[PDB]
Image (cartoon, grey):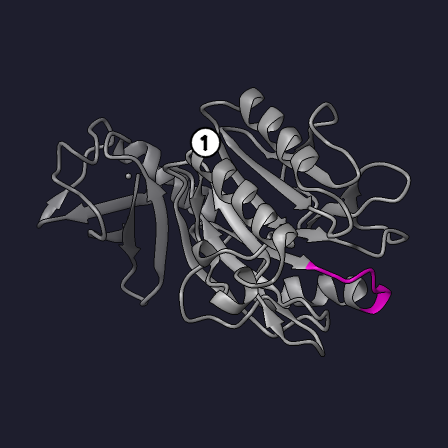
Amino acid sequence: HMDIRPRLRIGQINLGGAEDATRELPSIARDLGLDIVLVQAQYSMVGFLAQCGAHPKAGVYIRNRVLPCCVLHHLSSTHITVVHIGGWDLYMVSAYFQYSDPIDPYLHRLGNILDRLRGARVVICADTNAHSPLWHSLPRHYVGRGQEVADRRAKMEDFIGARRLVVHNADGHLPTFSTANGESYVDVTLSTRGVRVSEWRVTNESSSDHRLIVFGVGGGGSMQIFVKTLTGKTITLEVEPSDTIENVKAKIQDKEGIPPDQQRLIFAGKQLEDGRTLSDYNIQKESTLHLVLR
């Protein structure tokens, strides 16, 4: 049974403290196939948010409650929620850098979080309330807007630099933040190096003034192979070069509940023995295997 998607789908949205925007989140997650939504300025009196403190302004929505998800209590606070998505090395951070406050304290805590999780795959979803060309702000957002705007910008970019962080906000997308005073880009999707983020986009799904950002996250450049049936079904699968045929067959079991002892995979006109690896058979990125039932 389980899942048709190969990788996790994530949302990121500042809900502007609105009950209605917070309460539409489950339907939006269902509609778009989101596993996790990293939220800021939630309406906190709801029942479905992992959130910390008395008046939280960051949290995580886990759509499917059976997904093993740990909230790191030692790394979390009202403005920053850290979760572990079990059970290898993927962590995620929802952060809200309140506009009324300096940015330094927030950056120091994020720094602390990154020290502790050194080496791990970490994704950070932050409403920065900062403007930088890194995430497609226009010159009129970060130049000639006063010293504080330039300082937030500078601190944010130094931090990104010092922690070797990757910004996944792509060119040619809608602004993340739309007010009566205009449009801006202040919502930022970061990761540590070697996290694979795909299909990053900004949507119009939420009724917040902020726009829901959506993207994909895998489990490992790890690759993608297409396991095809003769009925037209394609199982997309995240797999390492050195994983075994057996290991692949069990991926299919958990994804489709097909018993491995009744699975036959064929590549390059050759049946695949359980013992061997994806490399031994010269199976690389975007390769297509036949899955035959026996």
Q: Residue at x 64, y 29 (%)?
A: 108
Q: As rendered, which of 180 and 268 lies closer to the eye?
A: 180
Query: On the image, numbered disc 1 is attached to which residue?
Result: 162
Q: Farthest residue toward the bottom?
A: 180
Is residue 4 visible to the viewer in this orientation of the structure? no
Q: Residue at x 70, y 45 (%)?
A: 65
Up/down of 236 relative to 201, above or below: above
Q: As rendered, which of 258 and 242 lies closer to the eye?
A: 242
What are the residue bounds of the magenta stretch?
A: 14-20
Measuring from the top left, give residue 139's x and y in whole percent: 48, 66
Measuring from the top left, give residue 15's x and y in whole percent: 75, 61
Q: Residue at x 32, y 67 (%)?
A: 231
Q: Indicate the secondary structure of the residue bearing disc 1.
A: helix
Say few, some or many: other residues with alpha carbon within 10 Å of mark 1 (under 14 / 14 to 19 / 20 or more).
Answer: few
Residue 272, by quadrant, is top left
Measuring from the top left, give residue 204's x and y in whole percent: 60, 74
Residue 261, by quadrant, is top left
Up/down of 165 relative to 31, above or below: above
